[PDB]
Length: 129
Length: 131
Image (cartoon, rainbow over all chains, first blue to last red; front, side, top):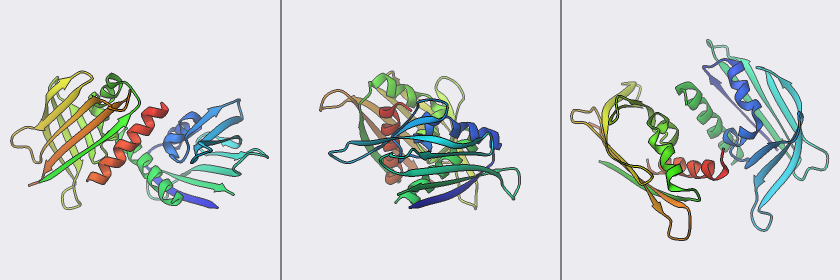
């Protein structure tokens, strides 16, 4: 399955990038996540809630791409429970001075939850949290 | 007349939760219907919300009517305010065991409850996870 959404924010791309690059904070931006822990420069352990008896489901993932102010991408490692990937892009918006943040997640309603998450993110940034 | 009340139990100490709410300028993160909250002095503050296209932004001055560390915070618009409103957040011991039950009551009267519920649930998740 694929989840894709985008929001334009009146802030520099470098500033929005830094927010996402802090992996432990991702569960704030993508609320379907319970926690993200840095294991090393490229690896991290991701966790999400899961009904009984599972409780939670965890897996490890690595960054496949990381370009300051431009993009951050990741994908679960071979053997991870839930096979998934994601990519966040920071692109100059056509209108005026703003950054379009494009988020695409894959795993093999979510769209509504991601929309809400991104709009919330937009709002906080544009008001100054 | 628009009254709203909700409560959520959170597995954290009262003082800590009270601490977040007491930071007035950060209230817009807790109560999403608010655009901004500005401190004017120990007891007064300026509140602002997003008004429909006809208008654009409506603000008024308010004052804290009660501030009991780790227990309660109450506020109310001053007379003449474009929008009459009051609020009260209590931090009570949760019956079950441990944890604090945050109770929020808001009243507004221009010249809702689902949004508050969502805001409170996110506040619960955020606090209980530590992010």
